[PDB]
Image: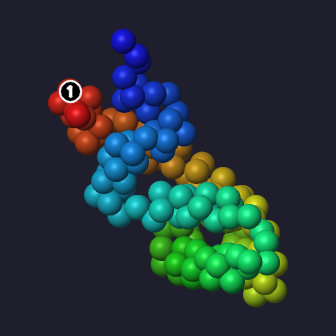
């Protein structure tokens, strides 16, 4: 009998985010707190970084980088913009403006947001009813 998933989610944020049920439960908790943008931004960067830089998907990667910049960086109100360093935001903005869209261009912002999650919402999620009750009666 294998170690149940909820125990791996308590090992690391990475294990939690590798599991469809854990992603859904973590995102629920963030929605209750008004921080779901942290998790969506985090997944958006991964989605972007895996696209192969080639001339055939250069429009695709460009609108995608623009969409991530527009939704999570440009928006000075949102939680992602307030939790990433100003120099990191200007750097990303530079890449967008000059159209230098290298696959790792969001990686440091993603690292800052990941740190934000491991410092507050991820430990809080592990003390939450959403998680603890999935532990008793989950499917």
Residue placed furthest toward the left: 137
Q: Residue at x 64, y 65 (%)?
A: 48
Q: Is residue 65 left or right of residue 17?
A: right
Residue 66 in view, yes or no: no
- Characterize the local packing of mark 1: few (<14), some (14-19) or many (20 or more) Cα atoms within 10 angstroms: few
Q: Measured from the top left, where is residue 32 in percent x and y? A: 28, 58
* In the rendered image, the vertical position of residue 6 relative to residue 25, given as above or below: above
In the image shown, does 55 or 63 lie closer to the viewer?
55
Q: Measured from the top left, where is residue 76 in percent x and y? A: 54, 80
Residue 136 in view, yes or no: yes
Q: Is residue 80 left or right of residue 135?
A: right
Q: Is residue 67 left or right of residue 33?
A: right
Q: Measured from the top left, where is residue 16 in percent x and y? A: 45, 39
The image quadrant of residue 139 is: top left
Q: Which residue is mark 1?
A: 136
Residue placed furthest toward the front: 56
Q: Residue at x 43, y 41 (%)?
A: 19
* In the rendered image, the vertical position of residue 65 relative to residue 50, given as above or below: below
Q: Residue at x 61, y 57 (%)?
A: 46
Q: Residue at x 48, y 62 (%)?
A: 40
Dot 1 falls on a residue whose secondary structure is: helix
In the image shown, does 23 or 120 lie closer to the viewer?
23
Residue placed furthest toward the bottom: 97
The quarter of the rendered structure image containing the N terminus is: top left
The image quadrant of residue 105 is: bottom right
* In the rendered image, the vertical position of residue 98 relative to residue 88, given as above or below: below
The image quadrant of residue 96 is: bottom right
Q: Measured from the top left, where is residue 75 in percent x and y? A: 53, 81
Q: Is residue 13 left or right of residue 106?
A: left
In the image shown, does 56 or 87 lie closer to the viewer?
56
């Amino acid at each position: 009998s294998p170690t149940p998933p909820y125990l791996k989610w308590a090992e690391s944020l990475h294990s939690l985010l590798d599991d469809q049920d854990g992603i859904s439960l973590f995102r629920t908790f963030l929605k209750q707190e008004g921080c779901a943008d942290l998790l969506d931004f985090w997944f958006a960067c991964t989605g972007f970084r895996k696209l192969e830089p080639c001339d055939s998907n250069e429009e695709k990667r460009l609108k995608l980088a623009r969409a991530i910049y527009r939704k999570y960086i440009l928006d000075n109100n949102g939680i992602v913009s307030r939790q990433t360093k100003p120099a990191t935001k200007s750097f990303i903005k530079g890449c967008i403006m000059k159209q230098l869209i290298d696959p790792a261009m969001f990686d440091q912002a993603q690292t800052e947001i990941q740190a934000t999650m491991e410092e507050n919402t991820y430990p809080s999620f592990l003390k939450s009813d959403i998680y603890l009750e999935y532990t008793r009666t989950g499917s």
